Amino acid sequence: MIISEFDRNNPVLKDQLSDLLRLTWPEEYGDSSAEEVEEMMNPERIAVAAVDQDELVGFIGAIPQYGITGWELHPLVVESSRRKNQIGTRLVNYLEKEVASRGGITIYLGTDDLDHEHPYEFYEKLGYKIVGVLPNANGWDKPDIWMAKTIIPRP
Amino acid sequence: MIISEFDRNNPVLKDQLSDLLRLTWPEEYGDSSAEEVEEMMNPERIAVAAVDQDELVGFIGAIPQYGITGWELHPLVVESSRRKNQIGTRLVNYLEKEVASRGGITIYLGTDDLDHEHPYEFYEKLGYKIVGVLPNANGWDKPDIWMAKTIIPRP
Image (cartoon, rainbow over all chains, first blue to last red; front, side):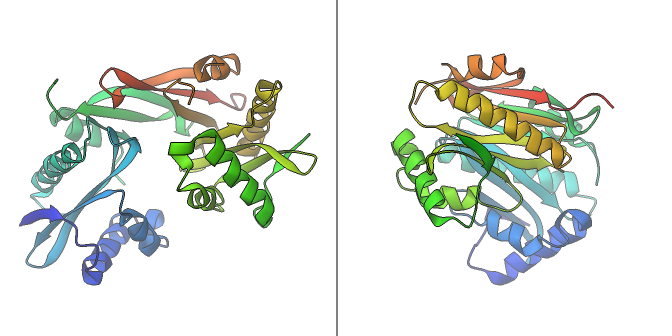
């Protein structure tokens, strides 16, 4: 497969991202599917696709939250398959390179660490470290964990 | 002055929020001023205005990030004046009530704690506690601090 910048002018690729979001998180994107995709296509954001045989099998994005130095990893969606983790890993590695090329220094993310491999385990193996916790985020005692990584060497 | 839900159908009130954002953070909203206001008017978000003599003197908003239980305080902008802190305080207190009424349990925020009273001091006195830190967020050693508060009693 190929990992590259998502072609925001390919309506079919956007339809597939839409279907991927809907099928992965029904009552989470089932209605705002197309709307979410448009948000993800915002020029300020980074958008990366994993394509195999002209089929979108994965997507990862990043949002510049603090200048162009601090970015939020969002979202990361990969099709169901036995190479899912490898797809995700390649998506993450490509994203870090993209982010760094736009002046990014650090990438953070928020996860409830639930399956809707545990997200925490996945990111921990990629070098991400817990930088914060929000209690009751998703409900009493149901926290959200924030993880981050400095994606470039100390100058 | 009066603190109440922002009338999203009042174009003059939106023009004033636009001017407030531009004048408070020139090279931060100087161009995306109107665009930022439209984002802030999104129906899912909470929008609160501080109005005095038909003049918008302050604004505070919240974004539902985790279901309807976890909300992000963003933004908080108050005009320059000697009652600025009191305006901000009343905005924050009204927001917490609004958030809680929509099923919210906790409110968090991110701050670089710089003046573009220190934001950290301001929120600390209102009951917000540090729940995380992102190093290099705004640049090397220039972190962003995340603060949060549970806005309703333990059931």
